[PDB]
Image 1 (cartoon, rainbow, N blue to C red):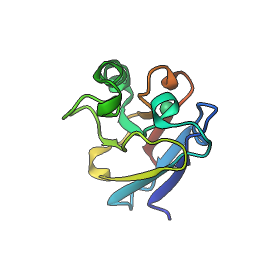
Image 2: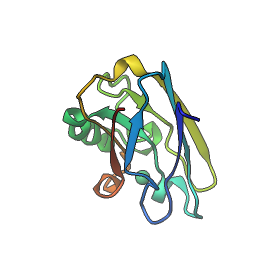
Image 3: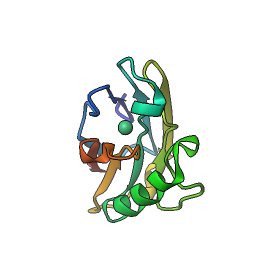
Image 4: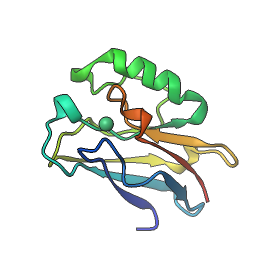
Length: 128
Ligand SMILES: [Cu+2]
């Protein structure tokens, strides 16, 4: 839809998009994450995590240290605007968030917090 995006994270440690623009008419925005491939969550799990660009590093840093069972995310992290679960191949997860949490002119980034993945698995999101 206009107010959602389907995104894939694959066994090549890559998202199939690196830029998302959100229409100002959207009250909510939904991201549907899926995982083509064959590798399980413990070696190639992906999540979709959204924060301001400013916060990306801190979110990734705390997440990796939080470990696998916590989906590589710090619990109750207020820097995170939206997050999916960490998924393995063949699994899928969605998240919806309020577009009011986005700001005009500000850059947000989405990324995977599985250790190292953010080297390639990142993109920008901003209001259209
Ligand atoms: Cu990943």
